[PDB]
Amino acid sequence: MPHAFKPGDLVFAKMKGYPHWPARIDDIADGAVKPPPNKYPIFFFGTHETAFLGPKDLFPYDKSKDKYGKPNKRKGFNEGLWEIQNNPHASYS
Image (cartoon, rainbow, N blue to C red; front, side, top):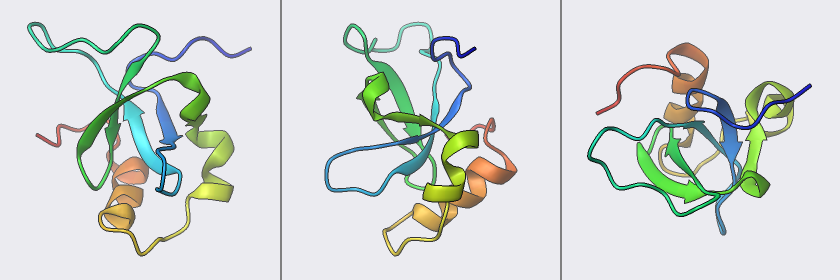
């Protein structure tokens, strides 16, 4: 059975106006700004941007890739597909 989301989990994350996007649950570094309650820090592959999202917008990657893991014309999307498949746990800083 599923657990709660934890750092390192791979997802597609949904934001308004954007396609379901390859992403990971990030850690919060010591001294870094914490997310709001019930939100997770989401690192978006390709764009390398971060947003705070709750579980309603997080789709586990294994289950969802057949639907959501196709190329898209949006900036950073195809780079992000490569990252989540090939080196999803690397430093992109």
